[PDB]
Image (cartoon, rainbow, N blue to C red):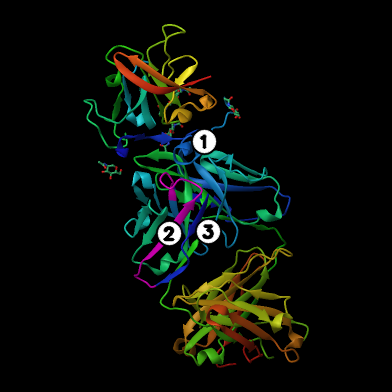
Amino acid sequence: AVLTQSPGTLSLSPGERATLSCRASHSVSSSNLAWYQQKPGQAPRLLMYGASRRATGIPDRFSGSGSGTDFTLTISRLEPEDFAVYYCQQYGSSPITFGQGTRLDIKGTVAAPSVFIFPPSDEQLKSGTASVVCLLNNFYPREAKVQWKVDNALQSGNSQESVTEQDSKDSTYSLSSTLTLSKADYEKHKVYACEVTHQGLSSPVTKSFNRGEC
Amino acid sequence: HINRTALNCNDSLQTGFITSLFYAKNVDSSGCRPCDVVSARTVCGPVYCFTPSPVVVGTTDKLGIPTYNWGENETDVFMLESLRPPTGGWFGCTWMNSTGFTKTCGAPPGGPTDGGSGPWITPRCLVDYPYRLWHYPCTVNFTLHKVRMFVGGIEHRFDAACN
Amino acid sequence: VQLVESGAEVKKPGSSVKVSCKASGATFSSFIFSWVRQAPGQGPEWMGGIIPMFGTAKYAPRLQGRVTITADESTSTAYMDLSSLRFEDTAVYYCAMEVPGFCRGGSCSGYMDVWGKGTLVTVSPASTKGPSVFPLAPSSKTSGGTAALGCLVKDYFPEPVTVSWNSGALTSGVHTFPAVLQSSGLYSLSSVVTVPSSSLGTQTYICNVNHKPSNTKVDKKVEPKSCG
Ligand SMILES: *[C@@H]1O[C@H](CO)[C@@H](O[C@@H]2O[C@H](CO)[C@@H](O)[C@H](O)[C@H]2NC(C)=O)[C@H](O)[C@H]1NC(C)=O
Ligand SMILES: *[C@@H]1O[C@H](CO)[C@@H](O[C@@H]2O[C@H](CO)[C@@H](O)[C@H](O)[C@H]2NC(C)=O)[C@H](O)[C@H]1NC(C)=O
Ligand SMILES: *[C@@H]1O[C@H](CO)[C@@H](O)[C@H](O)[C@H]1NC(C)=O
Ligand SMILES: *[C@@H]1O[C@H](CO)[C@@H](O)[C@H](O)[C@H]1NC(C)=O
């Protein structure tokens, strides 16, 4: 039984009604499905068992329903403490499985990222390694796509990304992407570019620099 | 010896009856057949028979050979008829089935002074046994009475849970 | 009911690790221990379970051959042993109170009620190490616009590192990103701040990095360069 949660990210305002869905590849016998809330740096907290039985200590606003292959977690009125990640979990089949999670964050107005690209410092190049950093500042929604190009060659698998926690005051996110190269490979190429795709951009945005031209 | 308890438990109604077997939970009170052969695949937890005193019945095959398959195979059964007292006294058994329903077997009551089905010696009294409050949650406030009596030549010491 | 676990451990690829869980508030013999791990940015993954009075231990098929789960009735401590560690095994390892929904043949399955506080297990080839602090330089070419600058805090272990700007006098527009565990097994972190372009030649910007586990304190002035 494989669990698929929808939507990946759910953006709503405090006081609104939240409905999270968990879909199973096969029917979950006797509605053996649980729900968890996980805040950053903590263990998951059980909210709901048996699809609809609320765990003790859980507020009235949390409600569950569904059966078969379609289960729903409902938060009637969203409080500030309710923005977190939510996992479903089936215990109807012998190997229990978890869903991939739904992120419930604060709704805001669409804002394109500001994109900056940072070449490696001479100090780091003297150590034999090169880190190219691309910054996407204060954007919404959270989904964004960073593509690295090196002399117009698409980089795939040699970068790592990191996303800040959502700003409660304006609901924006920030992302940093590090492309790591050896000093040798860095000196072979000229144009280092960061192409960004985002809902707030009608067209992809590219920031780039030219090694040796600066 | 633990392999001889049937463990076919399936809480399809989210009542939490299985949780009482593994974790300490006091009973909530908001809610308060001939003994032949029972298939073990439909049994969850211990099987008690009450020849005056309570006796635990383990999983066997049809011959009576003890099996150790947790009652999972279709050949696993509970030979309740073998536990009957030879002198023809009162006899009964009880257990929990897969979906959390207390089942009983026993002779039909020949009168208000006759015995009940499971561990019900009296309409008002119940033979005490280690899993009484699991099968019979509403008998928590019942009073215990030590009982000594000879039935068919055998002395039986046990407790009775009466109102 | 509360579950306490062994402290964080760092292991090398190919090694093994043993996590222990102590259950207080309930009888150990009938306790249903579940081990659930969670990789950074992923969902929880069930590893296996043990009910001591039944002696049976169930395992997840993904790593059924690399995990052995044991329960010690003498000291009321269940253990999870994972061998032949890989880099993909870096995760937080939880033990939990499984509340059964169905049982069959000596084992049960259900939901997790009481979770352990979590045990971080990092698989990396290197030990306690101080970070290098490199500048993320803004362009040295502007007035009225918004510029970005920062520090790259690279190749340290373990967590955590604190980063402030100008000894705490600069807080608006500061973004310190979550650290990332590199392929080498060391953490790398970026901290940036957006500033008005007109201040690039007039205001000094210094990031203050403090890595207490290695007693490494660095104050690095970030200056504009030809590339920004
Ligand atoms: C617990 O018992 C219920 C009793 O019905 C099982 O539910 C059946 O599951 C099968 C699975 O293929 C369905 O085809 C049936 O239609 C279900 N019956 C009903 C009445 O809904 C359930 O599968 C059992 N749970 C486990 C884990 O075995
Ligand atoms: C456990 O006992 C209950 C007690 O009745 C059984 O429930 C019955 O199931 C049959 C299935 O065909 C229904 O027709 C009856 O209406 C049910 N009775 C009640 C009162 O609900 C249940 O089937 C038993 N479980 C097993 C696995 O044998
Ligand atoms: C008892 O059950 C366990 C686990 O299901 C199994 O390994 C063993 O072979 C069974 N039989 C005996 C006699 O222990
Ligand atoms: C038994 O007595 C307790 C009080 O000690 C009460 O809460 C419970 O409801 C009673 N049960 C029944 C079945 O009357």
Pointer 2 chain: C
In terms of sequence position, does the residue under pointer 3 or pointer 2 come before the other? Answer: 2
Q: What is the three-letter code of the residue carrying label 2?
A: Ser
Confirm whether circles 3 and 1 share one chain. no
Confirm whether circles 1 and 2 share one chain. no
Numbered disc 3: secondary structure: loop
> Disc 3 vs disc 1: Cβ atoms closer than 8 Å?
no
In magenta segment, residue A126: no
Numbered disc 2: secondary structure: strand
Label 1 CB-ligand 1 distance < 8 A: no
- In the picture of the structure, the residue carrying the numbered disc 2 is C20
Q: Nearer the viewer, residue C40 or B86?
A: B86
Q: What is the three-letter code of the residue carrying label 3?
A: Lys
| B156 up-or-down from C43: above or below | above
Q: Which mark is residue B14?
A: 1
How many dots with numbers? 3
- In the picture of the structure, the residue carrying the numbered disc 3 is C117
Disc 1/disc 2 C-alpha distance (Å): 31 Å
Disc 3/disc 2 C-alpha distance (Å): 12 Å
